[PDB]
Image: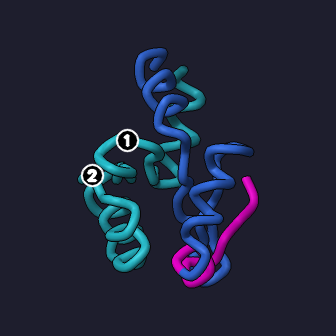
Chain colours: A cyan, B blue
Amino acid sequence: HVWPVQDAKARFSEFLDACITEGPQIVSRRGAEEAVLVPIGEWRRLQAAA
Amino acid sequence: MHVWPVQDAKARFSEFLDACITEGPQIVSRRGAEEAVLVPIGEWRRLQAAA
């Protein structure tokens, strides 16, 4: 579930489907986490739960 | 919370990621419907801890 930047770009459609079918997918740059793609409903729900 | 169609987030991935970090969560759409959001990782971790 951690994708190097170049992999998240080259396989972006797979990265987005994995987000929706498996859960949040992290993007890393040179092995350091940078961002995470979160399904939109889950994002909204987390904001309400926080 | 700018919205990027899937093909545009892919083609301009570096810009999409940069906007996430410099401006905040960026939405990705398919078929003109919001599907997911790219969130700075630190913001996500703090959200997780608070929920």
Instruction: Name the residue located 58 percent from the left edge and 41 percent from the top edge.
Output: A44
Count of number-bearing discs = 2
- Whether residues under marks 1 and 2 lie with C-beta atoms below 8 angstroms apart, the answer is yes
Mark 2 closeness class: few <14, some 14–19, many ≥20 residues within 10 Å: some
Q: Are marks 1 and 2 on the same chain?
A: yes
Instruction: Name the residue located 40 percent from the left edge and 62 percent from the top edge.
Output: A5
Asked if residue A15 shows in the view, the reply is no
What secondary structure is marked by label 1?
strand
| The residue stretch that appears in magenta | B1-10
The answer to whether residue A25 is left or right of residue B39 is: left
Chain of the residue where label 2 is placed in the rendered structure: A
**Up-down: is B29 above or below A41?**
below
Q: Looking at the picture, which amino acid does disc 2 mark?
A: Val
The residue labelled by disc 2 is: A2
**Up-down: is A32 above or below A46?**
below
Q: Residue A41 in the image: x percent, y percent? A: 52, 50
Q: Residue B48 in the image: x percent, y percent? A: 42, 25
Q: Residue A37 in the image: x percent, y percent? A: 45, 53
In the image shown, does B14 or B35 lie closer to the viewer? B14
Mark 1 closeness class: few <14, some 14–19, many ≥20 residues within 10 Å: some
In the image shown, does A4 or A2 lie closer to the viewer? A4
The answer to whether residue A12 is left or right of residue B15 is: left
Q: CA distance from mark 1 to mark 2?
A: 8 Å
Task: Identify the image quadrant of residue A3.
Answer: bottom left
The residue labelled by disc 1 is: A33
The answer to whether residue B26 is left or right of residue A20 is: right
Q: Considering the image in quadrants, where does the C terminus of chain B appear?
A: top left
